[PDB]
Amino acid sequence: ANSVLFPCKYASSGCEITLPHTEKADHEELCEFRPYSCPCPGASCKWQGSLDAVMPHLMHQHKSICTLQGEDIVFLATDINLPGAVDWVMMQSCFGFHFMLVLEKQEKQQFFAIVQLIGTRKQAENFAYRLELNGHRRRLTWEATPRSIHEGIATAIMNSDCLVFDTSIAQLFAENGNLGINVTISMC
Amino acid sequence: KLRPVAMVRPWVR
Ligand SMILES: [Zn+2]
Ligand SMILES: [Zn+2]
């Protein structure tokens, strides 16, 4: 025995990769056969399952998250001026997939807006999204590739890899304490 | 474009 390749921990659920211990743990974080965890902000929920199962999980356990059909919508976040750590979530359905639209006000204050595909990293690469804030002869735009829920959004948000704005920018675009984000999804 | 508007209610952590 010159050396040995070890199977990925998720080999049981179908990973055929075999690797030397050195880069086993490296593969096992990237591995696509890794179960999906709950993609809602606030991890009061600790559900796991297969990708097929996720949409149903949200449909049963997160009924208050609501969905819109369209490749162009307006995500109207209400009570934008609420103090402290706030979340806004909704779902956008188009091109046969479901996307999670997230806004996060963090405490210091700063807002972060980002879109994730309910799908795989490879699938996420087929899509682009635009976020845009609008006011009288004023527009702020963000354009990026959506993250797979597999990857999540937490590190993106930490790295400011998304639309970022502060409370004062919010006031240039907010009407009656509500902010309208124009979300547009497309293929590429 | 033809744009459906959806109102999203906040959740405080
Ligand atoms: Zn694997
Ligand atoms: Zn959940």
Image (cartoon, rainbow, N blue to C red):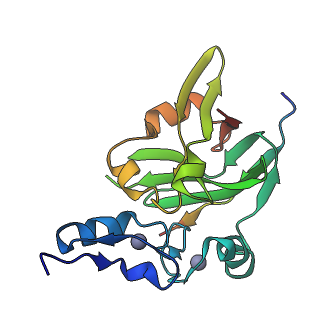
Q: Quadrant of residue A171?
A: top right
Report the residue that reaches farthest toward the top.
A137
Q: Quadrant of the C terminus of chain A?
A: top right
Quadrant containing the N terminus of chain A is: bottom left
A72 or A133, which lies in front?
A72
On screen, A53 above or below A154? below
A180 vs A63: above or below: above
Determine whether A142 is above or below A177 in the image: above
Q: Is residue A131 left or right of residue A26?
A: right
A81 and A157: which one is in front?
Answer: A157
Q: Residue furthest right?
A: B2
Residue A178 visible: yes
Percent across and percent down for residue A56 are: 73, 76
Residue appearing at x 55%, y 43% in the figure: A125
Q: Residue at (63%, 60%) from the top-left corner?
A: A118
Q: Splitting the image into four quadrants, where does ligand 1 fall?
A: bottom left
Occupied quadrant, residue A161: top left
Horizontal arrangement in the rendering, residue A163 relative to residue A27 (left or right): right
Please give the name of the residue rendered at 39% of the width and 49% of the height, measured from the top-left corner: A156
User: Horizontally, is A23 left or right of B8 in the view?
Assistant: left
Q: Nearer the viewer, residue A165 or A47?
A: A47
Report whether residue A81 is seen.
Answer: no
Residue A123: x and y in percent read 60, 50
Q: Is residue A34 above or below residue A110?
A: below
Q: Nearer the viewer, residue A185 or A15?
A: A15
